[PDB]
Image (cartoon, coloured by chain):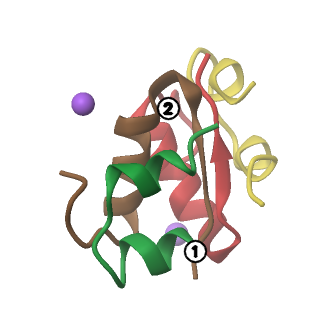
Chain colours: A red, B brown, C green, D yellow
Amino acid sequence: FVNQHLCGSHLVEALYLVCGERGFFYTXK
Amino acid sequence: FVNQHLCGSHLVEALYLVCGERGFFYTXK
Amino acid sequence: GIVEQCCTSICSLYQLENYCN
Amino acid sequence: GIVEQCCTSICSLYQLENYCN
Ligand code: NA
Ligand code: NA
């Protein structure tokens, strides 16, 4: 699911799934 | 959509919608 | 943290915006 | 930033993990 163009909520979703309990930071763009 | 219990991807989604171009940080937990 | 304020208790716009950049 | 690497170009696990805490 990570090896494609990911934009907006699609990108946020990937960060959420990959980073897990680590959490993440997102900034647009 | 913000005034409820929001967990996991539901919470991440709310941050995404509210913060917009500002971006956000999410940490679980 | 945000999970305590928004997941195990009811979230608010006020609290969400604390986690915007 | 992440949008340049993952949205306007093809994302990778390597790049995503750069934005984990
Ligand atoms: Na997974
Ligand atoms: Na809105």
Which residue bears the numbered disc 1? B28
- Which of the 4 quarters of the picture holds residue B24? top right
Which residue bears the numbered disc 2? A6
Mark 1, secondary structure of its residue: loop
- In the rendered structure, the residue with mark 2 lies on which chain? A
Asked whether B5 or C12 is in front, the reply is: C12
The number of callouts visible is: 2
**Few, some or many residues within 10 Å of mark 2 (<14, 14–19, 20+):** many
Left or right of residue B11, residue C19 in this image = right
Point out the image quarter for the C terminus of chain A: top right
**Does residue A1 appear anywhere in the picture?**
no
Q: Are marks 1 and 2 in contact (CB under 8 Å)?
A: no
Inter-mark Cα distance, 1 to 2: 22 Å
> Which residue sits at x=57%, y=34%?
B23
Q: Is residue D21 above or below residue C3?
A: above
> Which residue sits at x=28%, y=73%?
C10
Mark 2, secondary structure of its residue: loop
- In the rendered structure, the residue with mark 1 lies on which chain? B
Q: Is residue D11 above or below residue B5?
A: above
Q: Position of residue C20 (x, y in %)?
A: 56, 41
- Three-letter amino acid code at the position of disc 2: Leu
**Few, some or many residues within 10 Å of mark 1 (<14, 14–19, 20+):** some
> Which residue sits at x=34%, y=49%?
C13
Asked whether C2 or A17 is in front, the reply is: C2
- The yes-or-no answer for disc 1 within 8 Å of ligand 1 is no
Nearer to us of marks 1 and 2 is 1
- Which of the 4 quarters of the picture holds residue C7? bottom left
- The answer to whether marks 1 and 2 sit on the same chain is no
